[PDB]
Amino acid sequence: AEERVVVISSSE
Amino acid sequence: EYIKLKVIGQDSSEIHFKVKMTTHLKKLKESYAQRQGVPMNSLRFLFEGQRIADNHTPKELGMEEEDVIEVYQEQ
Image 1 (cartoon, each protein chain N blue to C red):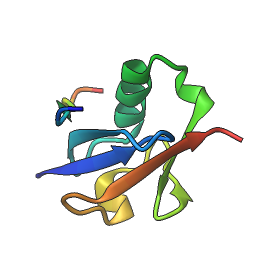
Image 2: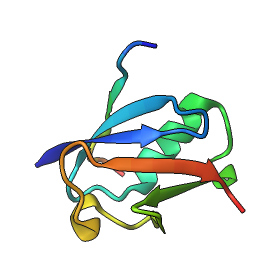
Image 3: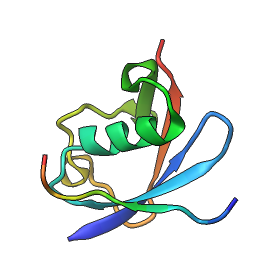
């Protein structure tokens, strides 16, 4: 598996 | 400030999340469940063995860069 980085936005 | 958290799954796979220190971790839980293709409520998310609440922030839990979250099946 490759590296997976998810950016979580600040809007909720 | 953002930090990168490592989420370790039941099968030892990893997804990392860049999360703002003030973001409620509900958002990470939703994203992880979406990417695993399972309902968010089938999972429990633990930091140092303690359950992460929807409205916990990384700041409240004292999380730091490269801290680990573990995902288990809900009991």
